[PDB]
Length: 386
Image (cartoon, rainbow, N blue to C red; front, top):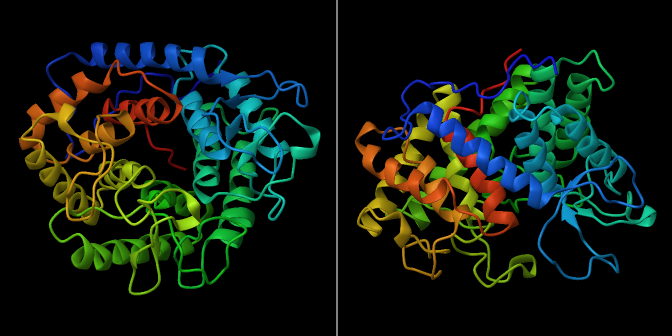
């Protein structure tokens, strides 16, 4: 109710193309439909330890210090952005969003209280028990800026103030490093050189700058672009890809089994699969030329690699382009499609990719990121401006 940016905003960002063999109404309809399916399967509000609290059902993870993980802050972030964007279509959007925010603040980090602990577990003891994960807080904080522009901050929750506190007292204080990179979480060092590229949400950082006036975010953006290029020119000169995790300076791929996540932490794997969308959005929304450069390189490589067939994309690649994965999943495919929207000569590829993703349902991770990608490439992810 009282949406100032009701769905569908269907914006047309300069220099970018959208799938064009279907109408905008068809694009919007595909998104509405995907959302209803996503919401029904993943949006939850059954926490005995937190009535009125919402979260996004993640995959059956391992033992989280004895607790049973139901979701993560990263899922919380995806859900919160999705929810605010669908406001206008989903009449219960603000109620759901405030419920997601309730969970995010109740399950605050055990280190920096202005951030969210990365695990959602149905227990009072788990509330304020876990430390943070940088990407979760980045999406959550960003969602608060969207909420502010969507409903204003005069109601029950002061979206803008909450955003500013989270951005400055949380993310900047604990995650922005001394050499202006982004560390892995509030448990990580202020001088840490360990970083996760999928955390380089350039377009999010632009908004942070615009809503706080803190130039710190601009210097972080510029440094990260420098780091990306320095990294790629040496380790991915023919693909433009980046690894799940990056370490040291000059930046280099993290070793295998980094943080015990997987043996491919040194390559373009599940964490990195999200990077193409995070980067391209900066060019689309703010016209950053460095974003278009990085996007076109990756886009052209993947197109040639699959001979223009998105169904040939696999879930994982070595930095030199050699296959690691074996099948097409949305978290990998969709971002590759989004990274292709800055060049009009990729229209057919964008059309084929859209057809592949629009109704692709599989699991929490791919589905959630696919919806975010779909929202963006259809012009329904508008940008918050003061």
